[PDB]
Amino acid sequence: CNVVSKDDWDGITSVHIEYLTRPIKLVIIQHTDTPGCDTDDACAARVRSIQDYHLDTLNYWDIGSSFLIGGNGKVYEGSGWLHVGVPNYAYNRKAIKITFIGSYNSKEPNSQQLNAIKALLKCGVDNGHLSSDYKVVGHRQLLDTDSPGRKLYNIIRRWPEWTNDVSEYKDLEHH
Image 1 (cartoon, rainbow, N blue to C red):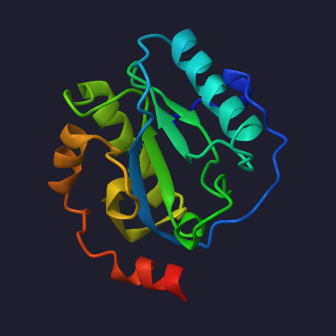
Image 2 (image 1 turned 90 degrees about the vertical axis):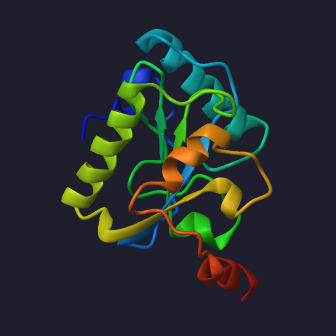
Image 3 (image 1 turned 135 degrees about the vertical axis):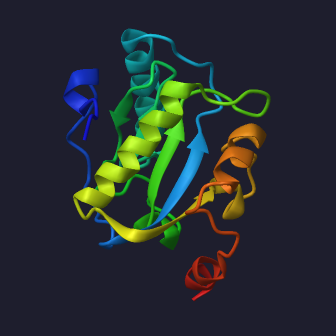
């Protein structure tokens, strides 16, 4: 996949490892709720800032998204296809989490961002990281948040992979 590796954005690769349950049947769309980024360098710096914040202040195992999509249309490797960033909630062991760098309550991601996630998901299915019948939700469907943002959420609701049913995941959390 066309991903910018952790080493190419100078991230911290030595993290505590916990594993996603394969194959993955759930994708959670987020936004960072931060300013956007227009260049490779600015997006790299933002991804670094987020990983530093998650590691050192929130004490996550790694950055809290599997992949991050900057306004430049590039995907930056987060916890990746295999590993877990957020140590709480059972659904974080059963979902690939893709966040868009920026805030998308008032505007949509641009054309290269949406193309980028389309290609990323298709590559995940090609590699078997993602089962062919994976479902898509916005983080707001599982957590009290506006993430991924009103406009982006309205976008993903119209994807064939979206689903409004999360009862299995709520139930898994309760159990």
